[PDB]
Image (tube, grey):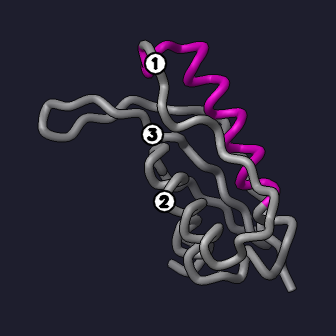
Amino acid sequence: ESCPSVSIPSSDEHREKKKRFTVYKVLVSVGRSEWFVFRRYAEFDKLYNSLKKQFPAMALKIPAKRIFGDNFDPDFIKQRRAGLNEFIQNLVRYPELYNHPDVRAFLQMDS
């Protein structure tokens, strides 16, 4: 029984097809191994919806999805990062959740 510890210390800006998007640099730690996994907001949202369909009764919060304005505003990104970090830290509080195959793949815990 080894519970993962996670955090999101920073975010970076990536590009695909000349189009900008933000990735959150997620630090994962299990036992004495640690690694980073990059995940953008749409992926956290995808994980959340999936988990919410399976367990429609948890009170897990995910930051807002529809933003009116500059979604690259630094203050906005920093607040979004804090919200995403709270979300994942609550996920790992429950073995029922951190052992779920989608959470493990999201965090690359079985690589």
SS for dot 3 = strand
Camera-side mark, 2 or 1: 1
Q: Residue placed at 25% from the left, 35% from the top?
A: 15
Camera-side mark, 1 or 3: 1
SS for dot 2 = helix
Which portion, as a residue range, is magenta?
70-90
* CA distance separating discs 2 and 1: 21 Å
Between 40 and 13, the one nearer to me in the picture: 40
Between 75 and 70, the one nearer to me in the picture: 70
Camera-side mark, 2 or 3: 2
SS for dot 1 = loop
- Asked if 60 appears above or below 21 in the picture, the reply is below
Would you name the residue on which mark 2 appears? 46
Q: Earlier in the sequence, mark 2 or mark 1?
A: 2
Quadrant in the rendering for residue 97: bottom right
For the residue marked with disc 3, what is the amino acid? Val
Few, some or many residues within 10 Å of mark 2 (<14, 14–19, 20+)? few
Which disc number belongs to residue 23? 3
Q: Earlier in the sequence, mark 2 or mark 3?
A: 3
Q: Earlier in the sequence, mark 1 or mark 3?
A: 3
The N terminus - image quarter: bottom right
Please give the count of numbered marks on the rendered protein: 3
- Give the x, y percent position of residue 89: 79, 54
Few, some or many residues within 10 Å of mark 1 (<14, 14–19, 20+)? few
For the residue marked with disc 2, what is the amino acid? Lys
**Seen in the image, is 36 located left or right of residue 9?**
left
Would you name the residue on which mark 1 appears? 68
Query: Cβ–Cβ below 8 Å for labels 2 and 1?
Result: no
For the residue marked with disc 1, what is the amino acid? Phe
* CA distance separating discs 2 and 3: 14 Å
Q: Residue placed at 48% from the left, 59% from the top?
A: 46
Specify whether residue 72 is painted magenta. Answer: yes
